[PDB]
Amino acid sequence: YDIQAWKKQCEELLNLIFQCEDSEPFRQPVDLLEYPDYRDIIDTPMDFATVRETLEAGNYESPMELCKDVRLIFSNSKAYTPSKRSRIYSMSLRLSAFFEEHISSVLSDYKSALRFHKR
Ligand SMILES: COC(=O)Nc1ccc(Cc2ccncc2)cc1
């Protein structure tokens, strides 16, 4: 029932994502010089360094907020892909499955801890 445990659990999950070769296109903001029309399609850019920085700044209140930003990285990749068979999109699908598999217990434990706090 540790209400604060999610933060280090998220730091460790982010460390695992950074070690994954599938995260390489998503470690830094999309290069607008290489994809000049990117902001015509994508309203809110997001990447794993921004997520890590937001967490380290103490600007996430809950793992649900972190999860919303990580999910935005994947929906941006799906929205920008010209094909469902593109390399970067295919990497986002595997990385998304890995993320969802690992974030599930973080979300469950935090919500359980908060319910216990308000029992
Ligand atoms: C400096 O790193 C980048 O610019 N990385 C990157 C990440 C996503 C995209 C967008 C995309 C393209 C094709 N399929 C799916 C999504 C482009 C580039």
Image: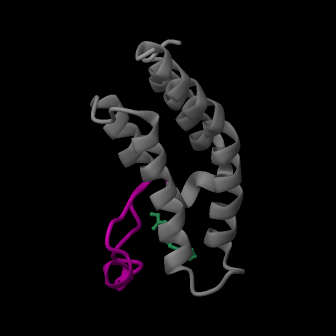
| Segment colored magenta | 27-47
What residue sits 51% from the left and 25% below the top?
110
Which is the main secondary structure of the residues drawn in magenta? loop
Q: Picture quarter containing residue 36?
A: bottom left
What residue sits 41% from the left and 80% below the top?
35
What residue sits 32% from the left and 73% below the top?
43
Q: Position of residue 75 (x, y in %)?
A: 51, 67
What residue sits 57% from the left and 87% below the top?
82
Q: Is residue 92 above or below residue 112?
A: below
- Was residue 88 drawn as part of the magenta stretch in this picture? no
Q: Position of residue 12 (x, y in %)?
A: 56, 27
Q: Nearer the viewer, residue 103 or 86?
A: 103
Q: Is residue 68 above or below residue 29?
A: above
Q: Is residue 2 above or below residue 93?
A: above
- Was residue 31 drawn as part of the magenta stretch in this picture? yes
Total labels: the figure holds: 0
Q: Is residue 115 above or below residue 83?
A: above
Q: Position of residue 74 (x, y in %)?
A: 54, 62
Left or right: residue 1 versus residue 62 is right
